[PDB]
Image 1 (cartoon, helix red, strand yellow):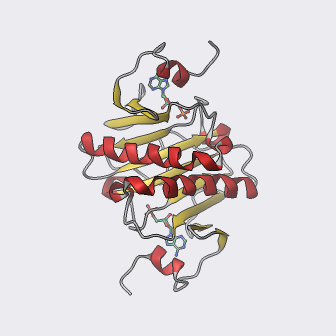
Image 2 (cartoon, helix red, strand yellow):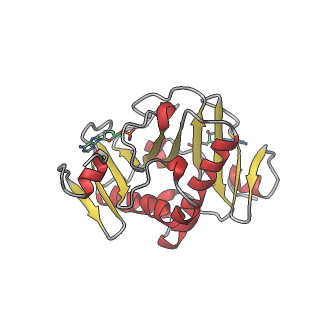
Length: 113
Length: 113
Ligand SMILES: Nc1ncnc2c1ncn2[C@H]1C[C@H](O)[C@@H](COP(=O)(O)O)O1
Ligand SMILES: Nc1ncnc2c1ncn2[C@H]1C[C@H](O)[C@@H](COP(=O)(O)O)O1
């Protein structure tokens, strides 16, 4: 293969508990949760990182946030949540396939790392 | 007025150092920076928080991330960065006008708050 972990999730080579799926994206629970609710929203299109996303990806990127919103509501995050994108080394990025974290179910602190 | 701080920035009632502006959004440095580079990207359209954004706002929300990318590059964040959206009480949201943080210039830690 040679793709990323999230490429493998998309092709059902690596398992994941999927909580939302449409023709453009998937959402699934994070394997190493940092809050009582912690899930990821990823595009099915491969983009390695936000710093190489293109202008015409705007609708797709916003779609990740809207899906994040919908999933947060489904999971009962009525007191709020935090969305995060990690870019590159200083962002702590591990998986080079663009994705959004959504964390909630506890008070989130500041700074955000 | 009765609007938010960022509503006031948009109408030039509260000052800000603006680093990007187009017909849809503004970006400016955060007044309480948590990293050597810390700026915000906001839509000119008022949306109180991400949890009430609508499907047809997807392009606008993605535009904030693309502008964040462009500004990060302008500011020399070649080692990476983190993007953050704070929603509601648990997200620590202070200003009820949708916006994206971009932080870089240091190693960002985990969890992200
Ligand atoms: N197999 C699997 N299932 C679910 N979640 C996973 C898996 N592998 C890694 N992860 C999560 C762990 C991190 O929160 C994120 C990668 O770091 P980042 O900094 O976001 O690139 O993705
Ligand atoms: N006047 C002004 N200029 C620039 N930045 C400002 C100003 N007032 C507040 N802020 C920043 C401070 C926080 O990082 C964010 C609000 O918290 P949040 O959790 O993001 O809603 O907005």
